[PDB]
């Protein structure tokens, strides 16, 4: 699933570099639907929120 993979991967980068990247990425692709997930308007928005914290804790399963 693309949506979960981009969520998981974007969350990973924002988890390492900090939430300062969430803002950058969100505003850098605000019109692009590939990043619509970063806004609360998307259904998986809540899923991504968890991924960030999870990658920071270093417990989640990286993608394949």
Image (spheres, grey):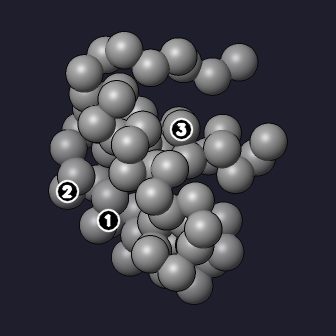
Q: Quadrant of residue 35?
A: bottom right
The one of 19 and 58 positioned closer to us in this rendering? 58
33 vs 46, left or right, is: right
**Residue shown at 52%/81% (left/top)?**
41
Are the residues flagged by discs 1 and 2 in contact, CB closer than 8 Å? Answer: yes
Crowdedness of circle 2 by 10 Å Cα count: few (<14), some, many (20+)?
Answer: few
SS at circle 3:
helix
Are the residues flagged by discs 1 and 3 in contact, CB closer than 8 Å? Answer: no
Q: Position of residue 38 (x, y in %)?
A: 46, 66
The one of 37 and 35 positioned closer to us in this rendering? 37
**Residue shown at 53%/38% (left/top)?**
8
Return the residue at label 1: 24
Return the residue at label 3: 8
Tell me: residue 3, above or below residue 33.
above
SS at circle 1:
helix
Are the residues flagged by discs 2 and 3 in contact, CB closer than 8 Å? Answer: no
Q: Quadrant of residue 20?
A: bottom left
Q: Nearer the viewer, mark 2 or mark 3?
A: 3
The CA distance from mark 1 to mark 3 is: 17 Å
**Residue shown at 29%/67% (left/top)?**
23
Q: Position of residue 55 (x, y in %)?
A: 35, 27
Q: Position of residue 15 (x, y in %)?
A: 29, 37
The CA distance from mark 2 to mark 3 is: 17 Å
Pointer 2 or 3: first along the chain: 3
SS at circle 2:
helix
Return the residue at label 2: 20
The one of 31 and 43 positioned closer to us in this rendering? 43
Q: Nearer the viewer, mark 1 or mark 3?
A: 3
The one of 54 and 22 positioned closer to us in this rendering? 54
Crowdedness of circle 3 by 10 Å Cα count: few (<14), some, many (20+)?
Answer: many
Q: List the single residue furthest toward the bottom.
A: 31
Pointer 1 or 3: first along the chain: 3
């Amino acid at each position: 699933g693309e949506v979960r993979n981009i969520v998981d991967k974007t969350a990973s980068f924002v988890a390492r570099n900090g939430p300062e990247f969430e803002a950058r990425i969100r505003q850098n692709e605000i019109n692009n639907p590939k990043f619509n997930f970063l806004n609360p308007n998307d259904p998986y928005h809540a899923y991504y929120r968890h991924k960030v914290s999870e990658f920071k804790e270093g417990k989640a399963q990286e993608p394949s």
